[PDB]
Image 1 (cartoon, rainbow over the protein chains, first blue to last red):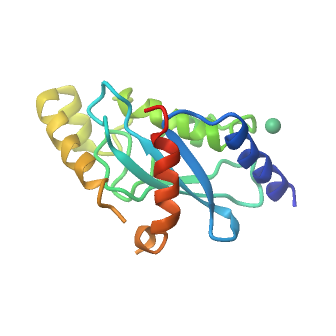
Image 2: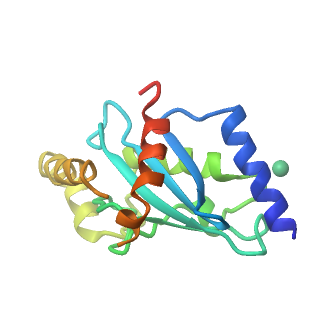
Length: 150
Length: 21
Ligand code: NA
């Protein structure tokens, strides 16, 4: 199928041009479900976090974006309670030129650049705007938790 | 549940993501 042919190319690109601070691979023997890891970027409240995600593709990929969820506990204005991510390029701004590598690096960039007008987590959105001191403390807890996560 | 069952797989991914950090 076209989706499976595309996903083998996504995987090869990750090996040839490895992105810094992120990684992804198929789970077990299923090409349509991937595991992924994103490191919290240095110089941010998320620094040193080792966050685990799952990516689910459909047979309509790359014409349809995959669904991406954090499995690790998260505290971020654009991340829902169930780990789902409000990021424009994973919804209405999706393009077939994006792949696993670019999706992961886009999510990585979102961690230190939250969108205030999309409050998926209303408390994280409020603290980020009002009390940035308390925002970093709440993010610190989930950084620690991401280390003994499996 | 999921993270625990795929412990080995996630640790390989953590090691790959750590490089150059
Ligand atoms: Na392409």
